[PDB]
Amino acid sequence: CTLKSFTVEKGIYQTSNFRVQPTESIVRFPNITNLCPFDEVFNATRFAS
Amino acid sequence: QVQLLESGGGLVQPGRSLRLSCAASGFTFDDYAMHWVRQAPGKGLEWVSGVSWNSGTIGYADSVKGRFTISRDNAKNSLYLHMRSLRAEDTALYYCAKAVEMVRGLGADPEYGMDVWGQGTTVTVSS
Ligand SMILES: *[C@@H]1O[C@H](CO)[C@@H](O)[C@H](O)[C@H]1NC(C)=O
């Protein structure tokens, strides 16, 4: 297929690409410590007028 | 230093309005539930009204319910007390006090501990 012919002469030919495939995915980020103070808004004891 | 300055006093006839103002300076005004407490002349104290950290009022005194109207403003650090149906029995000093426990610092949210007190005004009514 690479030579675009059916008769191939004696010799060494370089054809294609060997490339090992990935296994899975990885995502990294440190311990999530900051947190928006939402509860104080929704869970407040008394809302304004 | 923490400062609580109130203004609005002066003789007004019965059946009018007034608008007392308390301004706070020296702390994060949005983590402290304010209170307005009267002080009759030569008598004991008497709770009047309050307001929580989120501008939500916490009810008024039983004998005053119907006229007083509290309001807050965190942007200008200002708490206001509109007063209606003024009658002779409403002459007294008025302090604006602040709570102690900062909100979410430990069950429920805090409202006790009137610790810092400004020097009150001298509202009076007569004809
Ligand atoms: C972040 O969480 C991991 C997993 O619970 C823990 O091992 C680590 O001690 C935490 N953060 C640090 C670096 O203390």
Image (tube, coloured by chain):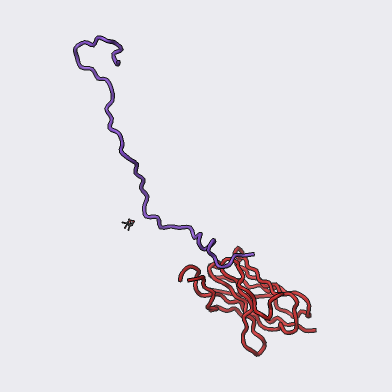
Chain colours: A purple, B red
Reply above or below: B56 against B87.
above
Residue at coordinates 54% horizontally, 61% vertically from top-left? A42
The residue lying toward the viewer, choosing from B34 and B119, is B34
Q: Nearer the viewer, residue B124 or A42?
A: A42
| Total residue callouts | 0
Farthest top residue in view: A7
In this view, which residue lies farthest toward the right? B127
Q: Residue furthest bottom?
A: B42
User: Which of the 4 quarters of the picture holds residue A4?
Assistant: top left
Residue B11 in picture, x, y percent from top left: 75, 81
- Provide residue A28's location: percent of width, then percent of height: 35, 48
Image coords of residue B41 (percent x, y): 67, 88
> With A7 as the anchor, is A47 left or right in this view?
right
Name the outermost residue toward the left. A10
Residue B42: x, y in percent? 65, 90
- Which quarter of the figure is the C terminus of chain B placed in? bottom right
Residue at image coords 61%, 85%: B45
Viewer-nearest residue: B22 or B51:
B51
Quarter of the image where ligand 1 sits: bottom left
Residue in the image at 70% along x and 81% along y:
B123
Taking the image as shown, residue B61 lies to the left or right of residue B84, namely left
Residue that appears at 59% across and 78% down: B118
- Splitting the image into 4 quarters, where does residue A33 fall? bottom left
